[PDB]
Amino acid sequence: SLVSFLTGLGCPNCIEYFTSQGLQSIYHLQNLTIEDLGALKIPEQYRMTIWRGLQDL
View 1: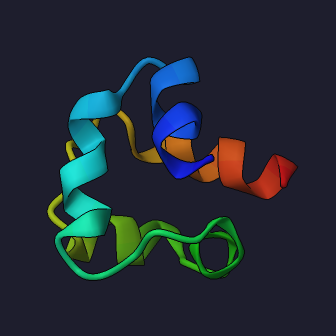
View 2 (view 1 turned 90 degrees about the vertical axis):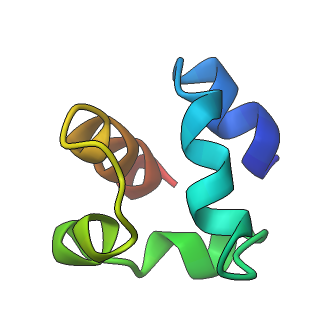
């Protein structure tokens, strides 16, 4: 789901950022903040995309 998620959102290149920290679940992924995404060195371009998307779930 994580892999599909980032891909169906158009940012499979963001996958490493999460799996690099041991993040692989969608649950855990939802309670991250916009600041968290930034700490996870995620490109300022996909931050809200992802964040918004995770809010939806």
